[PDB]
Image (cartoon, rainbow over all chains, first blue to last red; front, side, top):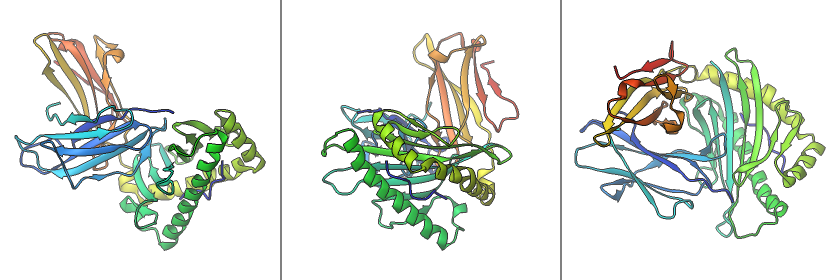
Length: 9
Length: 100
Length: 275
């Protein structure tokens, strides 16, 4: 499983 | 902008044997950016039922794709992969050489 | 006996041909097990290995939501990066992200990683301690400040040390027969004259898994590394890999040249000879 939503750059 | 040229390899899944079904692969790797045109050719003509892997990339960020089709080798038919990419000033054709 | 799980994400802007293309793939070791493509008809995270197919609908619905959420963030990022680099609207750009974890032969955590590239070069990456960032340029320092203020590394560490390796474990066991196997390379060398005074010697390894392998040529015992052509390790299509290395040699000197193959499924490294 993937991580949760990545934080924007 | 970074550009990296595709290293193109054309080959069969198993050792080729005339009259025996096999898979013909065109593996393209090491390229950037990801936009690429790849075709498998039979006697110079585009093969229409060609599948490909999902776009992935290596440790150094360069992209790789596998294109492939089921085929049955014969003595007369010639196979190749045609590739176009921003690094290639003309499309590049690599012929299947079964005797490497 | 060592293992890894990694997710790979690519997004490419196509200004004036719509929304950025988005592709996500997940691998355990060298075996792909999931994909998502923004342009496909399904709009679902989909299985790409038989052992992931047993996951229930909560798995598929959850990963679909998460991956579509990754897609949106990259769509934002593309906008933000253009601004950071003062780049124009009418060129295509590429964002790439990869993350995941490694475990040892005992399945305990070794290493975690989370890195990002823009237009094919390093942009920002979590360092080995999972507590700090390596920023590649000044624009990436701006991302660094924003990610430190938002305590991003701490949330990532929790994933890479906990969740990531829990699911890797689960996959290694559900996918036992294909992921915990080792197929040793079947090896040989070919010889072909290129003229009446030289020959191509090529060292072949076929049908092996995992993909990692070393192939080298020696001449009277010394490495011929600068004279060797070594191709990229390539998929056969059936789950195994192939690789070759070649040298061009004066005819008559074949018996000075040996090929050496190292792979984890070999009991001993092999030496192939012309006599």
